[PDB]
Length: 241
Length: 242
Ligand SMILES: *C(=O)N1C[C@H](NOS(=O)(=O)O)CC[C@H]1C(N)=O
Ligand SMILES: *C(=O)N1C[C@H](NOS(=O)(=O)O)CC[C@H]1C(N)=O
Image (cartoon, rainbow over all chains, first blue to last red; front, side):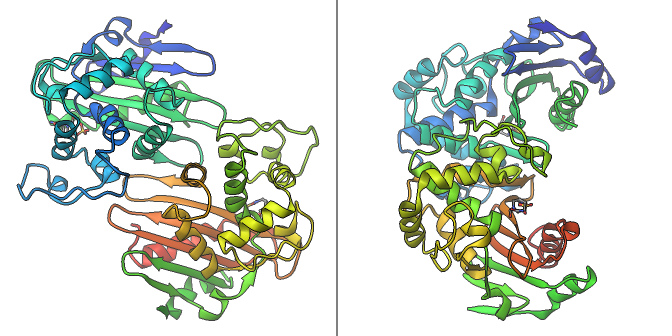
């Protein structure tokens, strides 16, 4: 591990506070601007769709990435939620109601088991079975996110290979002739401190770079900064052109 | 049901080129092309053959997974990116012929033939060298047949394991953003006339999938970038991508 305080400038520049954590898989070395915050545990929020998807698939609650989840007919704040979805589009548009339903069908007991098996964060499910990742007892740090993601990448989680491959497909965010990004965004709004998350990895020809960032987010105005700042660090470290 | 629409020829004309683009709307089950006749003309698949080759290699265990390393044989070749170690992902990306030759040798004539017949792939003919028949042998496929093949792949309906099909689709990943995902493979038939360039694959949207297959005359390697550029001009035109 290495602290690299120079990255703070990217935060400073956007009048922001937070942490970016980076792991070099070939060299097994981590890098971060803030070793203390990198180990600070927060609510996972919508980053919880990763393990939730995994569990739903492995238990057959979700058959596959094509299965349609019908809108319940209730209009909500985010327009893209008000329509039918599959796993691919539910992940992309971060469709809460679909993931709530997954969680209800999974159930308290099986959800607890799976998180303990995943070694995920503090493994605590206290709260509502369908919102505990948003305002219940579960907490995870950036470094623990990486550790989780590394298992997922290598297909080493205690779920089927197939489930893991489907989720990684659903995490696809960006790809071109230089890199592939698989990742998931999040915004913890109910409990202070309000924070934005971006976690995932960058795939290169020769290596893989895992990432996990969070940043203070008092309003939804700054959301774009999750990606923008992470990329500024990736460019700096010459991981992406 | 197919529709000809000759307006797309302009995109070829504008780059002082000849060829065909074929499009298939999966939701509507309708095809579109600028040239119905060329769309059904069969050509050597060349490097587009890496799709079914990858599939077969995986399904038989010749390739364990997308991470398995294929060591460079130490012979320096024309294309610099081939002169290094590769996995399935990078071998597909940089279209590394020697790796795919080795796969083919290990697969063998008999198993390769059975699999292609089972895939209903092109004319199903393997005549020629077991490791180059897709480049100078007897195998031939049309753009429409490419689509029909790709459609089976997309729906996991080929006669190989689900896992193999998923891995290959992953390896076909070319481009992705917030508007579309493109999974595809390029090709350049150089040994036998007519020299042609290929691009085949599909465009994934939130709500639909658009399959594509194009080929175009390619007397020199100068025009290679036009495979993608022209295809995208049609896709823009039809408002499939922005
Ligand atoms: C997830 O954290 N949420 C669902 C949705 N996600 O958008 S995000 O992934 O860009 O963060 C809106 C924010 C959040 C929520 N309030 O439930
Ligand atoms: C494949 O058709 N080939 C291998 C490599 N691929 O290039 S391409 O995919 O961009 O078309 C070079 C061309 C061709 C060959 N010479 O064998």
